[PDB]
Image (cartoon, rainbow, N blue to C red):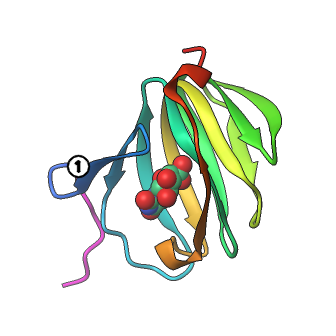
Amino acid sequence: MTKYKYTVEESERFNKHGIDLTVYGQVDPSATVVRVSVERGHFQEFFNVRSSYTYYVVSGQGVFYLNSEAVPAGATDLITVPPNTRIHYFGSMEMVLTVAPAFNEQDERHVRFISESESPY
Ligand SMILES: O=C(O)[C@H]1O[C@@H](n2ccc(=O)[nH]c2=O)[C@H](O)[C@@H]1O
């Protein structure tokens, strides 16, 4: 009766600001985990007033901008962003993203769009 396993086949998959998200549909107030695929960048800067965003880099290479500070990232790195921190990123990467507490779109705030030409990837 308890659902323990979530598949890609049953996930919601969509493009948001230049990334391809795989939202499995985990419901758990403590944290939600999703997959992020990015070819060139996340062409939008945002922050979340409540949740920390932790990106594990499965493969590829990129650069995060966290409150405008460049943070290079490569395969096997863990990028840990606290709440209320402006986030965008460029790169060609596959990532596993944890949002803790659970992701709630009402907690996220739009700062700006970013031109696709800004990404060096
Ligand atoms: O976190 C990110 O880099 C991007 O992915 C989005 N996201 C992240 C987790 C989640 O469960 N659902 C989402 O839609 C977030 O809004 C942002 O655009």
x then y, percent, for residue 95:
50, 38
| Magenta-span inclusion, residue 5 | yes
Q: In this view, does 82 lie above or below 17?
A: below
Range of the magenta residues?
1-7
The reply, left or right, for residue 116 in relation to residue 77 is left
Along the viewing direction, whichever of 58 and 14 lies nearer the viewer: 14
Pointer 1 local density, CA inside 10 Å: few below 14, some 14–19, many at least 20: few
The reply, left or right, for residue 22 in relation to residue 41 is left
Q: How many labels does the image show?
A: 1
Q: Image quadrant for the N terminus?
A: bottom left
Along the viewing direction, whichever of 117 and 55 lies nearer the viewer: 117
x then y, percent, for residue 107:
58, 76
x then y, percent, for residue 28:
45, 79
Q: Can residue 104 be seen in this view?
A: no
Q: Image quadrant for the C terminus?
A: top right
Q: Is residue 5 above or below residue 39?
A: below
| Magenta-span inclusion, residue 63 | no
Q: Is residue 109 visible?
A: yes
The reply, left or right, for residue 10 in relation to residue 14 is left
Q: In this view, does 57 lie above or below 7?
A: above
> Which residue is depicted at the point 23% across and 57% down?
11
- The residue tagged 1 is 8
Along the viewing direction, whichever of 29 and 3 lies nearer the viewer: 29
Element on which disc 1 rests: loop
Q: Is ligand 1 closer than 8 angstroms to the Cβ of mark 1? A: no
The secondary structure that most of the magenta stretch takes on is: loop
The three-letter code of the residue at mark 1 reads: Val
> Which residue is depicted at the point 69% across and 35% down?
64
Along the viewing direction, whichever of 44 and 14 lies nearer the viewer: 44
> Which residue is depicted at the point 52% across and 31% down?
41
